[PDB]
Image (cartoon, rainbow, N blue to C red):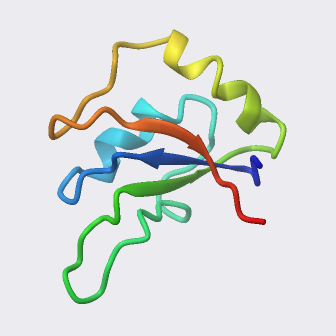
Amino acid sequence: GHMDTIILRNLNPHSTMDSILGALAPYAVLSSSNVRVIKDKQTQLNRGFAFIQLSTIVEAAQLLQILQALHPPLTIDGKTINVEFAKGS
């Protein structure tokens, strides 16, 4: 389920992770050493999903019912960031 990470889906191929970062990480204590939009190597684009790690596997589930209740609806490059969990087995 939560895996200490929230998948910022809809992550536009040219959105600046830096404007997305605080806009989806008021409590996740990150800057650079987590910021992985699964980005390519041939095209150097964001895949459409970023792995914002958390402070715990627990806080991830709770932040998903706090964050959107705060701040305006985030929309960069006309993509609403979706708020999915890092399901990996």
Q: Nearer the viewer, residue 57 or 47?
A: 47
Q: Please identify the quarter of the rendering in which residue 64 is found.
A: top right
Q: Which residue does the image show at 34% across and 65% down from the upper left?
A: 47
Residue 27 location, x and y as percent? 63, 31
Number of on-image labels: 0
- Furthest toward the bottom, the residue is 42
**Is 24 positioned to the left or the right of 75 in the image?**
right
| x, y percent for residue 59 | 77, 34
- In this view, the residue in front, 37 or 86, is 86
Q: Residue at x 37, y 37 (%)?
A: 81
Task: Please state which of residues 25 and 10 is positioned toward the viewer in this rendering.
Answer: 10
- Which residue occupies the foreground of this view, 20 or 9? 9
Asked whether, in this view, residue 38 is left or right of residue 7, the answer is: left
Is 48 placed above or below 54 here?
below
**Residue 36 at x, y percent in the picture:** 47, 65
What residue is rendered at 43% in x and 70% in y?
38
Which of the 4 image quarters holds residue 21? top left
Describe residue 48's horizontal placement relative to residue 75 as left or right: right
Quadrant containing the C terminus is bottom right
Image: 78 above or below 17: above
**Residue at image location 31% in from the left, 32% down from the top:** 80
Quarter holding residue 48: bottom left
The residue most toward the right is 58
